[PDB]
Length: 152
Ligand code: HEM
Ligand SMILES: [Cl-]
Image 1 (cartoon, rainbow, N blue to C red):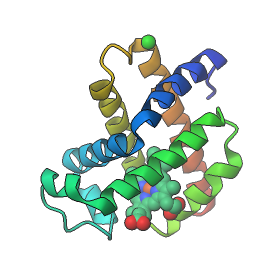
Image 2 (image 1 turned 90 degrees about the horizontal axis):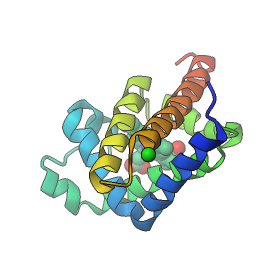
Image 3 (image 1 turned 30 degrees about the vertical axis):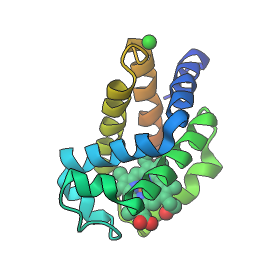
């Protein structure tokens, strides 16, 4: 699949809004991920002992991990699909070091869209939502192809 230039514009304007508060968006996304799909928390050895949303919001380690994930996703999105070099190390680490199945990438994609809706009422309409869904689907499909090459 491919996104049109119009669709990429929609994605990057939304992302520039995320960049006004990377840490807050990353906290909200990880917390939504763990509340909607609690098994995903087991993959995060650094903070899988956290038990409540209040503990998650207070965790400096969780916030840093959210910043790192959103920083990398923003860099990838800015490549507008020409992301082969940037995606390679991420697919490698998530397949073999962190052991993240594709379904967990689907779960975090759902969490991303929900947090964008929640944080940007009136500025995340049907076109931007559809474009962001396509951008995240392309990201997952391109990771899944690298997973396949690694036999994961
Ligand atoms: C938008 C999707 C994601 C992006 C862009 C992303 C990005 C990153 C980056 C850049 C790192 C640090 C460098 C590296 O190890 O490659 C990282 C680490 C990690 N990621 Fe992801 N990630 C995503 C989704 C996920 C999901 C869904 C999970 C688990 C359910 C996950 C689990 C981890 C773990 C456990 C680490 C190591 C964290 C630590 O140091 O404590 N990632 N991720
Ligand atoms: Cl829109």
